[PDB]
């Protein structure tokens, strides 16, 4: 899905956006060409080569990283063991924060 | 795995054998990366130099899988002396901050 990918990618230069595509093509291509002792294509039988979203996700996760920086690392590092509900104060605090967010949103 | 970071303080009167016991317990871990810092190898440095050295020592530990580090004679790291009292705040903050930063993921 193109729109989903566009939503996922942010702070991406055009060169990054097209390198992402190149990397996805590269991994799909490698899928059907493999040999270690020698080199050999998949008997040219991979004429139905199709690129799946999984290739794009793997590339976006391991291949192409924006230079402008991101904020996933901080989120994952700060909320480590998640949030559980042991008492009302948690709900009260979350509600109050939401109220203040609404305040600043529409003041 | 819930607690990738663990700390511990050995305490006792002077001339007890703390340093040797720490070294032995560290040795019997069979870990890949082990390091033993100490005031003895930076004597006469200024505060900035000590902070740089502590930075460089800790940075290495972040580039392994599992590691153990030793900090002996803390009272010398920061120049404590009863009269006053007088000491270095910069090194103290370096230590306090560094003792609550978990390493990269899966380490
Ligand atoms: N069971 C033991 N416990 C402690 N030290 C021992 C023991 N057996 C032998 N030793 C010897 O005792 C000495 C330990 O002195 P060490 O300087 O390590 O102690 P410390 O209390 O950490 O000293 P410092 O106050 O100078 O930092 C070493 O010579 C060590 O070989």
Image (tube, coloured by chain):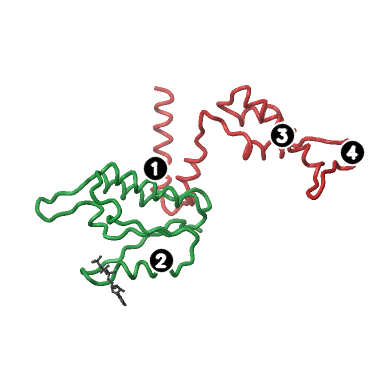
Q: Chain of mark 2?
A: B
**Position above or below: B79 against B16:** above
Label 3 crowd (10 A; few <14 / some 14-19 / many >=20): many
Q: Is mark 3 within 8 Å of ligand 1?
A: no
Image coordinates of residue B96 in percent, x first then y, are: 31, 49
> Mark 4 falls on what kind of element?
loop
Spatial CA distance of label 2 from label 1 is 44 Å
Q: Residue B26, which numbered label?
A: 2
Element under disc 3? helix
CA neighbours of label 1 inside 10 A, class few (<14), some (14 to 19), many (20+)? few
Task: Assess whether mark 3 and mark 2 are in contact (beta carbons under 8 angstroms).
Answer: no
In the rendered structure, are the residues bearing label 1 and label 3 in contact, judged by CB atoms less than 8 Å apart?
A: no
Q: Choose mark 4 or mark 3, whichever is in front.
A: 4
Q: Are marks 4 and 3 in contact (CB under 8 Å)?
A: no
Which image quadrant shows ligand 1? bottom left
- The part of the image, by quadrant, that contains residue B8 is bottom left
The residue under the point 37% across, 67% down is: B23
The numbered mark, 1 or 3, whose residue comes first in the sequence reads 3
| Residue depicted at x 59% and y 23% | A13
Depth check, mark 2 against mark 3: the one in front is 2
Residue bearing mark 4? A44
Task: Count neighbours of disc 2 (C-alpha within 10 A) and say few if under 14, some if 14 to 19, many if 20 or more.
Answer: some
């Amino acid at each position: 899905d193109i729109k989903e990918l566009a939503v996922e990618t942010k702070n991406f230069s055009g060169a990054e956006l097209e390198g992402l595509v190149r990397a996805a093509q590269s991994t799909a291509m490698n899928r059907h060409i493999k040999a270690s002792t020698k080199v050999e294509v998949d008997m040219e039988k991979a004429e139905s080569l199709q690129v799946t979203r999984g290739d794009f996700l793997a590339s976006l996760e391991n291949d192409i990283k924006p230079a402008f920086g991101t904020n996933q690392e901080d989120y994952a590092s700060y909320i480590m063991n998640g949030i559980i509900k042991w008492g009302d104060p948690v709900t009260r605090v979350l509600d109050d924060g939401e109220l203040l967010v609404q305040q600043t949103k529409n003041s | 795995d819930r607690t990738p970071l663990v700390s511990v303080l050995l305490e006792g009167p002077p001339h007890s054998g703390k340093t040797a016991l720490a070294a032995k317990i560290a040795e019997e871990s069979n870990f890949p990366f082990i390091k033993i810092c100490s005031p003895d190898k930076m004597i006469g440095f200024s505060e900035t130099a000590k902070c740089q050295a502590m930075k460089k020592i800790f940075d290495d530990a972040y580039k392994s899988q599992l590691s153990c580090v030793v900090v002996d004679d803390i009272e010398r790291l920061l120049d404590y002396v009863p009269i006053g009292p007088r000491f270095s705040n910069l090194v103290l903050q370096a230590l306090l901050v560094l003792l609550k930063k978990a390493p990269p993921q899966g380490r």
